[PDB]
Image (cartoon, rainbow over all chains, first blue to last red; front, side, top):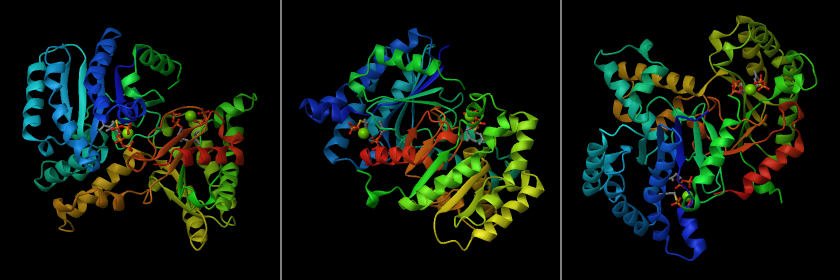
Length: 221
Length: 226
Ligand SMILES: CC(C)=CCSP(=O)(O)OP(=O)(O)O
Ligand SMILES: CC(C)=CCSP(=O)(O)OP(=O)(O)O
Ligand SMILES: CC(C)CCOP(=O)(O)OP(=O)(O)O
Ligand SMILES: CC(C)CCOP(=O)(O)OP(=O)(O)O
Ligand SMILES: [Mg+2]
Ligand SMILES: [Mg+2]
């Protein structure tokens, strides 16, 4: 039957544009509309959570023009999802983002927190290393103030401290043809089924998603 | 095509498909398992010839305790054969995972194999035995908490580089992960260490995995090298 939580690595947007002879920014403008479209399709099929990798903690090393474009563009989050019926959370280091963007994100989380349908977790300035490190520093802090012991440290305690919460992804889908997780949900993908496709994210449609879910259903866990 | 000068330095290996391979020939599950170490040993020899410096192979996970008591006890007793298999191989052998939850007899087989092969200057084989990714991260974290509370480090020293040194599987991390048996998951293997690792999944069952399948994986890896 249906995977309840799908993790999504949204790769291939720049290649999509360059191969078509478009400006790289054209690739990026399909990001949120496409993701929204996948949320609608996934919602009808009975999927409960999508966790989508939009910007990793390593993407600051991209060309300043592209980083600047992406950071302005990410402010369009509110228009795309405020009135969508999707419940939106952002994970990742929000305090590094421009303050306009931090406000925009907080507004989107606030306005959509009552929504009862699909939960979209957007990873923005996120990395798996980062997630495990903030968890660890929170666990150390508490041990230094006698709020927990060293024998209390277990899988469950970590699942509490991490930003991406249980239940973990059933299926991970990565577009763009690369076969890596690129510092996405490291701890959380321990038993996740991986599906890699050469299809670039702006080309990823309803049939591509169904092909992926059909592929997942055939696998014995 | 295989570029000798661009060999991955570290290959990780999920040795899956042993039970199915046996049952696909109607044999008993135990007969599949007996191929594990001889195959692994052959893969080391092949890999050594190519210039690969490290292999980390998943032999038994922290979840595999949930299996059939007879399968588990046969595995634990079979694992003691690592000394016979590897002590004269020329491979340097290390084990990662929770040694003290194993049968004491196997703990001593391990210690002797590590001691016996520690002077070997070629390929380094790391056998992950009663290991998991969660386990590695949790044990690193306990270690860091113990140091924190004994004044041995500050909470401010907690960064990626620190975690790299506390984890059992060390730098350099795997360039390439090979999983036999057709499943497309990492099954709680080297989670932190696989953050940028290229994944290669093959339907070939582990006991049928040969030099050609390995070379195919490496060529594959070299054509998607970023
Ligand atoms: C949206 C972001 C920052 C990354 C995924 S798309 P991309 O920028 O990596 O583009 P390409 O993979 O290079 O096609
Ligand atoms: C080497 C060990 C202990 C497990 C991997 S082989 P396996 O028992 O999982 O065999 P199957 O996946 O069931 O074919
Ligand atoms: C969509 C996303 C930010 C995750 C993929 O990120 P990336 O392509 O920038 O990192 P890689 O070069 O390792 O693939
Ligand atoms: C080789 C290995 C110990 C990992 C694969 O075996 P496993 O049964 O622990 O993991 P799976 O249940 O996903 O097959
Ligand atoms: Mg990319
Ligand atoms: Mg298996």
